[PDB]
Each structure stands twice: as structure tokens, then as C-alpha cells.
Image: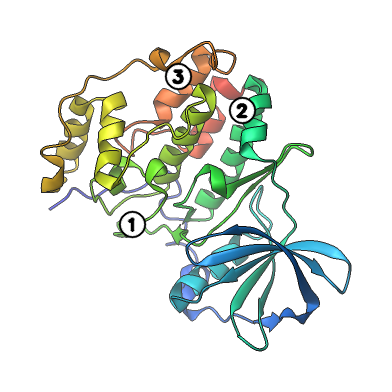
Amino acid sequence: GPVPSRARVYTDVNTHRPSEYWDYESHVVEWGNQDDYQLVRKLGRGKYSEVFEAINITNNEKVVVKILKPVKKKKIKREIKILENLRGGPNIITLADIVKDPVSRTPALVFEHVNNTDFKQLYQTLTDYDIRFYMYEILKALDYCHSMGIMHRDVKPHNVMIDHEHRKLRLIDWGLAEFYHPGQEYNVRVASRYFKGPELLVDYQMYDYSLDMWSLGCMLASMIFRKEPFFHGHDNYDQLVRIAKVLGTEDLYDYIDKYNIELDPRFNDILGRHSRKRWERFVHSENQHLVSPEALDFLDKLLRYDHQSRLTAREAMEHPYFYTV
């Protein structure tokens, strides 16, 4: 069978905590009354959620309300517990209340207000310093949630709210997040296609916090190179091919041999043979003001097939790329 793996950092943080911390199924949710809130406008729509801007009528404060389509109770309980545990953490969205509609009884999570500058409008005005600053802000959130024994598992631009005017970053949508247990096999059907780490695409279940570091590297590559998404797969199998076209097929075979991963037969005719590309190739006139030797060295240390070889969030925070922040 496949070779077992464990996180290089915060490996046993959950093992040493009481069951109440990670045992979300046994968590007692106290569902409040939705009447304290009035819906104002739609902010976004997810697979099983709808997000609204709302007003708390008891204090005239704007809030964000996430209305959940209750397809699985275990998933709702998991998200709430994680949110509760992370509550107050740096750059983590803040759970304010848990409410249900007195009539439809549809579950809803109430968050402290979060503003978001449009990504296209931000993309054009971003400087090398802004990328470093915001990347450091996301690392604070990731090092914290990893230190709290949690993996986000859905790191992507749409889950990173940035209010550029106030220089505020919030990591949102903890609905796919999970508690890390050393040696636990996880479902690989997580994260958005473009941000899926090689471990998910090769069906290697014993992954850890390093999955979030791959996702972060994808966002950084798209930001510094002005190429959204950086790895543009058309399906989950093609996603691995788009990674292989940049990282090469040699290091992919070394990764699958190291962990004794059995590659699905669907890869045989599509992988091909690809050389490892130099990061400098993606540099052009339109993106050179965001690229530097430090940025490329940092990216090279995040975007590695081997999840064990990737920088941890704490190691990433000590990289020369962040000396100016």
C-alpha cells in the first residue's frame, strides 16, 4: 500500500488536546434567533451557501450572513466548531452568531463585517510591496490555524477577502476545513481545481497542512506573473498535466515512487513527458515590476510535488521575500 506521511510541524497538537476540541460531532450548537438581523443585499453564492450583507437591528451594525443549504449536518457542525475554535485568530473571519430562521429553520452563520475590494480593480494597482504585505497577512492566518491543528483545504482568491483601503485581509469559508490527526486518511475531493495539490490529484489521502501551502503558491504565482489561474486544468486529471508542464514529469514520478502512489489508468495517455521549466520563463514586460529573485526563490519552495519538501507557514514567514514587511 501507500507509504504513510505526517506533518513536519504541529503534528500532535490535536492528540494532546481534549476530545471536545476536535470532536465536532459531539459539539452542542446553540442556535439563536434570526430576528435580530435584517438581510440587505446578496454578496455571493456558493455550492451549498448564499452570502448576504445584513444589518443587526439591535445596534445598527452591518454583519455578513451566510445561509447554508443543509445537505449534511456533520459538515455544518464541523464548520461551526472550527469557526468557534479559531474565533479571534489573526485574519480569520469572525463568527458572531449562529442563527436559524424561525419559519424555514434554515441554518445561518453571522459574521463580523468584512469588506472586499474587487480582484480585477486590485490586480491593476498592486505593487511588489502589496503582494508581500498581503501574502504575509495570509501566512499569519495559516500559521495560526495550522498551530490550532486545522487545515483550511480551500485556499483560493475567492476565500481571501481584502479591503485594500484599510489594508485588511480575512481568510473566509471554513466549510471544507478539517482537524489534522497524524496518519488520518482524508477525502481528496476538496479545494478548487486550480488550487488542488498534487497529493489530491494522485489520490494520496494522508495529506496535511502542506496542502494549504501548495494552494498559497498557486495564488502567489498567479499574482506575481499576472496569469489567473496559474495552473489552468480543464478537469482533475488535466490539472496534474498542467502542473507537470511546469514542474516536469521526472519529479512527479519521483514523488509517486517515494510514497508508492498507484496512479489511476486515466493518466497513462495524457501525462506525456515534460521538462522542468525555469521560473524566469513566466516573466514578461506586463509582470516584471512584481517579480524579483526573492519572489522566485520563495515560489520555488512552495510549488513542490513532495508535500513534505514545501515550506511550512512559519518557515515561509522567515523567507527573505518578507524582509521588507
Residue 18 visible, this angle: no
**Up-down relation of residue 318 to residue 138 (above or below):** above
- Disc 1 secondary structure class: loop
Residue 78: image location, x then y, percent: 49, 69
Residue 169, numbered circle:
none
Check the image and name the residue furthest to the bottom: 103
Foreground of the two, 251 or 150: 251
- The answer to whether residue 123 is left or right of residue 271 is right
- The answer to whether residue 39 is left or right of residue 135 is right
Q: Do tag 3 and tag 2 residues touch (Cβ < 8 Å)?
A: no
Q: Amino acid at mark 1?
A: Arg
Residue under circle 2?
131
What residue do we see at 49% from left, 67% from top? 48
What residue do we see at 78% from left, 37% from top? 165
- Disc 2 secondary structure class: helix
Residue 98 visible, this angle: yes
Q: Alpha-carbon distance for marks 1 and 2?
A: 29 Å
Q: Amino acid at mark 2?
A: Ile
Name the quadrant of the C terminus. Answer: top right
Q: Alpha-carbon distance for marks 1 and 3?
A: 30 Å
Residue 135: image location, x then y, percent: 59, 33
Residue under circle 3?
297
Residue 95: image location, x then y, percent: 67, 64
- The answer to whether residue 76 is left or right of residue 87 is left
Judge the density around disc 1: few (<14), some (14-19), many (≥20) Cα neighbours within 10 Å: some
Q: Do tag 1 and tag 3 residues touch (Cβ < 8 Å)?
A: no
Q: Amino acid at mark 3?
A: Asp
Residue under circle 1?
189
